[PDB]
Image (cartoon, protein in one colour):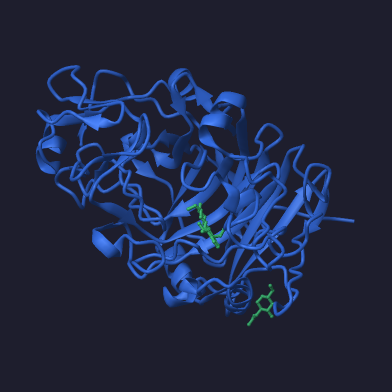
Length: 431
Ligand SMILES: OC[C@@H]1[C@@H](O[C@@H]2O[C@H](CO)[C@@H](O)[C@H](O)[C@H]2O)[C@H](O)[C@@H](O)c2nccn21
Ligand SMILES: *[C@@H]1O[C@H](CO)[C@@H](O)[C@H](O)[C@H]1NC(C)=O
């Protein structure tokens, strides 16, 4: 895609902190940038749309390469169009803004580079307010193995780069991404919604879901892929689980793991109020070259340090962190194939983490499964009483996009106090 000039692109500021054991925490002047899929796409020589609603202009975009040459991504009115605002340290992502639904942004080191986080033997910490984020919604904070420049160096067809949020990929190998590898994904374009469609290509990469949640339920989930970095896929390579990527991931959702009173409104982690979420990525030898061996989670709310809930499933060790063993036990017990292990487990996830990954923050609803996998029973044809079926208390009728968009359009998530660095250094304790 080309870079458009009709609308100035000003990235909202979102300060983060980098922390070390000896030096404590220091501010970084990071910013956020809207993902390219949400942007206006128009002719380089004017104002004519290359994409309107859910279809491409066949004149400007008769094929992927011609499209990318003819078409520019342009600047965004963050608040006005997409309901994205920042105080400078707190990011608010609103659900529905006019005809726009949801958003995704990436943390930037500067105006043309994503911040590249390397979190092996490190921790990531943030605050979240989900008080206005109900059933059916997902306020997500996660890592994707994108390139810092959004693919600009890799793909001659992409002259827009990170400044315009290009180069997305994740473990779902999404085919609804409009620009991939510097070409518009116009092949066999198929409408899937009023403003969405899919093309013949997907874009795959390893993904660490630090946070996927609403005020009813939350999950953290590593997703390894056999690839290395952002990879365009075709055919069965795009297929979830059987292809390049572990789309299911190895998830830890406290409720799914058999503790139904740990997280939610008025629970130990009280989702009706803001709280702090710490995620630590431990290696076997406590070095940044070691193998990722454990993902720990600690919560802080009202000054109280809250350890992660314990798994309570027959045939699963009662642990409270993600490990390769936990993952094998959980998959066996829930009846899910361990695609996680097949794609290389924590070691592969950690290799991705070590290579550096981009922070994404997003609010979305779910046209495929109504977010039932997050906060309800899933699959909808399995016995709810079976280990792993029940993930939340939301009704199985919840999360229909047309429903939530009508019913709770002003839902929002607020992500704040972003910090990362040495294990045990982004928060402190005392008696
Ligand atoms: O909830 C755990 C997974 C779930 O993956 C989840 O899908 C979501 C939608 O793509 C992703 O955002 C999550 O990161 C992923 O872990 C599968 O979509 C579901 O079919 C299933 N069945 C059993 C497990 N799971
Ligand atoms: C690594 O650190 C953990 C603390 O989280 C400690 O229990 C363990 O003994 C350490 N391992 C080595 C080899 O230093």
